[PDB]
Image (cartoon, rainbow, N blue to C red):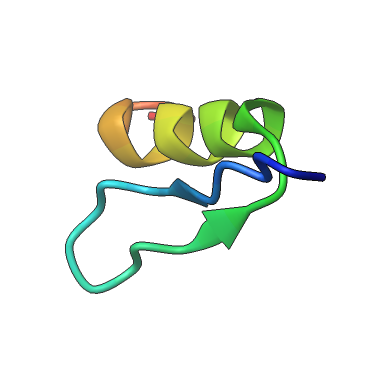
Length: 38
């Protein structure tokens, strides 16, 4: 699109990129909530 808006994840070393914020959400959620599954 005209404004693809590259969603750059704010994570150390990882900093992945996605097409939507949806994928960034789940991606960041697990990074931040490292306590998940524990």
